[PDB]
Amino acid sequence: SGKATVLAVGTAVPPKEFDQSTYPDFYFNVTNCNDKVELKGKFQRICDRSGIKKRHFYLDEEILKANPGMCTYMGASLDVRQNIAVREVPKLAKEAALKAIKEWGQPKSKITHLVFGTTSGVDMPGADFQLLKLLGLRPNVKRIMLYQQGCSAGATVTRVAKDLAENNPGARVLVACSEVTAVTFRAPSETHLDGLVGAALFGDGAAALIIGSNPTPVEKPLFEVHWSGQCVLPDSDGAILGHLREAGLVFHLLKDVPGIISKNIEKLLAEPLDYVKSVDEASPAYTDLFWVVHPGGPAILDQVEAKLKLDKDRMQATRDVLAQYGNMSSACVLFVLDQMRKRSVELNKDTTGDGLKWGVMLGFGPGLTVETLLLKSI
Amino acid sequence: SGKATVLAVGTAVPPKEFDQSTYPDFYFNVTNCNDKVELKGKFQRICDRSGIKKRHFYLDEEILKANPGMCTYMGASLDVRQNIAVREVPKLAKEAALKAIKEWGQPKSKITHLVFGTTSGVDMPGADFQLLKLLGLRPNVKRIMLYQQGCSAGATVTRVAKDLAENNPGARVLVACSEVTAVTFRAPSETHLDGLVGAALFGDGAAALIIGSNPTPVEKPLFEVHWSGQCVLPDSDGAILGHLREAGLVFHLLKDVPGIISKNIEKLLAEPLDYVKSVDEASPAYTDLFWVVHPGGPAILDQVEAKLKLDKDRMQATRDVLAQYGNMSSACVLFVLDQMRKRSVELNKDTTGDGLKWGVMLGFGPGLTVETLLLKSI
């Protein structure tokens, strides 16, 4: 009783779909890099093993032709990237939030808090303010705006909402994460091979939740958030860096991120599993939990699945999101939460979490930081 | 009681002091704008009525001469501004945090949460991570990184810490706000007269708090946080805009901020004063409260003081901070909190809030957004 509960989830993506099989052709063409045949061949191999069937993007050929700075490797281009991101990030969030608010079924006036996460642009007032205005929420909604957060922020916003909901009687928290890759897109370069990873994986999308404690009989709970933690992994300094520059957002990958996560995942889970033992008086195996994992890339999923000896179906909701949308940074794990519920209905599962009682939500980001949440299904 | 309690405050500024009386000479010289004699006269008048005696800055003539882009009006300069701010913002916060931790008197290992606010630069991992590392905090400290927030964020971080402390038994929250004006400094221009306001007011500084519920016998409470709210004021759309561009952070002032605040301040305070009436069965006049106000500029303070009919001493702690440090954006209101406690010792007051029981903490930022907290003195 009393635990922050997910009462709705909605998602949204830009309409234009980019097939992964032919994305190398598009990408090297629009960046005027067709003479880089060996690099294109490498990029094709990366895309072919990415686990991704398509991604959705706001950026298209027309916008890129109108803004040649964004088609360069490190040309000055932040102003145009910001123009795009500051406009489109709250608009995509609005679409997701309206879906979440419909599912919840209560009037918008009952929203008391708003937590907004993004890695795509910054502005003052922030995207939280813009979303408040776009939705016509009360002017005294309490906002928390989480900018430049990265891939762990879907878990972060859930952790933030948990304490808001639990400490404030009657509170109903609208959570939204929204990502548009206009700030990171750039030409491929032999001098930035780790850039090919992001170019193969990152896509656009937004997701929204309603979270509250003590659901009423007219609300419909989906997941309870029982425990939350955040930690920096050992021996991971500099594994992922992201710098916002005149050329936009640039990433650098300096360590084996899947290996570092896998090396530490059992230790990460000791604390939430001790919570479960306190409640249920026994220790589940890792494969006895459901899994809501940020699909950073296929190697993270494969290595965690192997390390924890998970049945192959446990990662399926995560892999389904990766396949249909790619890595949507902060929003991606919230799409997985939605897919977990959706497959529970279609596969006739006994609970919203793959028919299992307890589950783990994981987000990963620079630090290397891991966000862990213990979930209970409904 | 269990209310979130301020247990320590520490502050820090860059060492170099810039006398406000002679800042116009320095500013117009270093930007090579000495031929703009009428503009310099206007700036001198703004500085002379600013209520500021001095400000502290990390930026100095040597750094500006090394990086002449920052001495232009709108020349490309974000990369150097980011280099400075990403480095110096956590360093300044560390100094303030060490002072807060000393006053608190407990081991750093008892810090469970870290809330970091800034408007000065963005990076991944964030300034929160850098502070965690610089202080040698536990790797599983739960962090909230509030970037690009603006002048209301000192109140925002206190609001965030309140729910962390109250919802998590034993939680001890390190709050830090840190601002370095390297991101906003630029040449004066006859086409950007609102820029002269920021050039006259904004200074550098950092402040830190320890916040916890249920203080132990060896902790020493200073203030209790009893009520928190945030609201967008009516008819204020576009009053303050802040855009992060290839030229750094640019502000636009389009409406009368002091007038909008004073037009709405009584309405803002109705809910916290209703709380007071619920607890104390009494209705203090505004002048019966102590005041911890963001010193945005002298006009805000003068117009709020007149509207609420405050005795002139009520704004003194706020005006003392403005005089000695200028408007240090998110950190400034936390300096005022420290100054309120300092004057309570030196002026032999019966409580930490100017001898009064209940107090109002106010932050102001883009929206126009007002953060309001109700404090109880000790």
Image (tube, coloured by chain):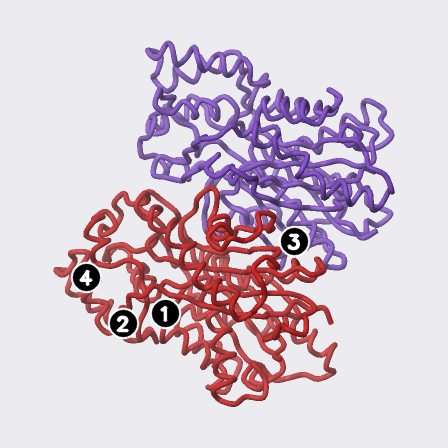
Chain colours: A purple, B red
Same chain for labels 2 and 3? Say yes or no.
no
x, y percent for residue A97: 65, 41
Type of amino acid at the residue the image marks with label 3: His
Q: Are marks 2 and 1 in contact (CB under 8 Å)?
A: yes
Asked which secondary structure carries label 1, the reply is loop
Q: Nearer the viewer, residue A28 or B101?
A: B101
- Name the chain under label 3: A
Q: Are marks 2 and 3 in contact (CB under 8 Å)?
A: no
Label 1: how many Cα within 10 Å (few below 14, some 14–19, many 20+): many
- Label 4: which residue? B28
> Mark 3 against mark 1, which lies toward the viewer?
1
Asked which secondary structure carries label 2, the reply is helix
Q: CA distance from mark 2 to mark 3?
A: 41 Å
> Mark 4 against mark 2, which lies toward the viewer?
2
Q: CA distance from mark 1 to mark 4?
A: 19 Å
Q: CA distance from mark 2 to mark 1?
A: 9 Å
**At 84% from the left edge and 45% from the top edge, which residue is drawn?**
A279
Image quarter for residue B285? bottom right
Type of amino acid at the residue the image marks with label 2: Gln
- Label 1: which residue? B326
Same chain for labels 1 and 4? Say yes or no.
yes
> Mark 1 against mark 4, which lies toward the viewer?
1
Q: Earlier in the sequence, mark 1 or mark 4?
A: 4
- Label 3: which residue? A113
Q: Nearer the viewer, residue B99 or A146?
A: B99
**At 59% from the left edge and 57% from the top edge, which residue is drawn?**
B109
Q: Which mark is residue A91?
A: none
Q: Is residue B160 visible?
A: no
